[PDB]
Length: 240
Ligand SMILES: NC(=O)c1ncn([C@@H]2O[C@H](COP(=O)(O)O)[C@@H](O)[C@H]2O)c1N
Image 1 (cartoon, protein in one colour):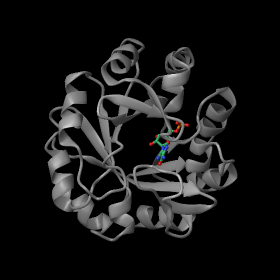
Image 2 (cartoon, helix red, strand yellow; image 1 turned 90 degrees about the horizontal axis):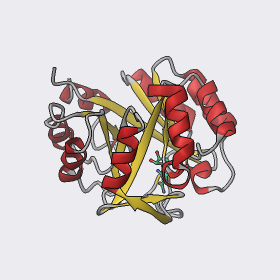
Image 3 (cartoon, helix red, strand yellow; image 1 turned 45 degrees about the vertical axis):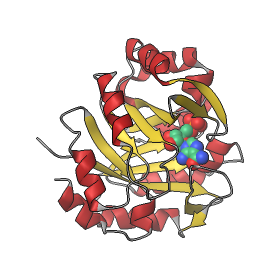
Image 4 (cartoon, helix red, strand yellow; image 1 turned 90 degrees about the vertical axis):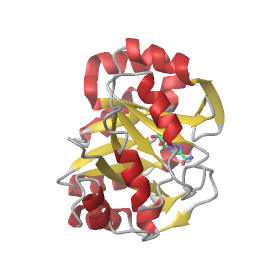
């Protein structure tokens, strides 16, 4: 069918639900309680929660106990990300019972570890590809980490189940999705692709939904929901 999955985002820094611009540290706008934000999305009919520990992604401590409390409060599917770079952080992340985790920096820095984790955990693992042009970025998007196509080829052959694709130039900007990049990634894999960053309107969600036949499975939405560009109910109606 034509349905696009919607994943409202809760990104956590210093115990707060925040949004960044280009994922730059220091551009936080705070939106209150991460737990109340997640409960509100769930109450409005969310099927998914995209939950991110940004302190862990930046290496400035973590919010592990709070993240765990938020995930325990969800009856819906949970996608968990942020600082998952070794066995201990992966163990705690999966212990939330989350539907899947996203690995970002680890795919660039420890490709052998990511290959091992894919083989042992299957589609509980997705890899986040955060892109500037055709260059991948890591460590909270503070450093380069490789070429998009070479990395996709490697992860394809390692059996990676799913990719989360962010154009860093769109992220947090309300400037719309990068539909060319999404289609370019769909051309390079037969794995489901989740779009992330830039959504600003219901027309943006409809345009991403137009790529479902090409292999786009879902869209993560952050700033536009916190900014009340539309309600989650309106977004769910638009993507059904
Ligand atoms: N600067 C940022 O906003 C940022 N840096 C990383 N992340 C998210 O955190 C994850 C990557 O963390 P790590 O690089 O530890 O795997 C990815 O899913 C990515 O969307 C961000 N939102």
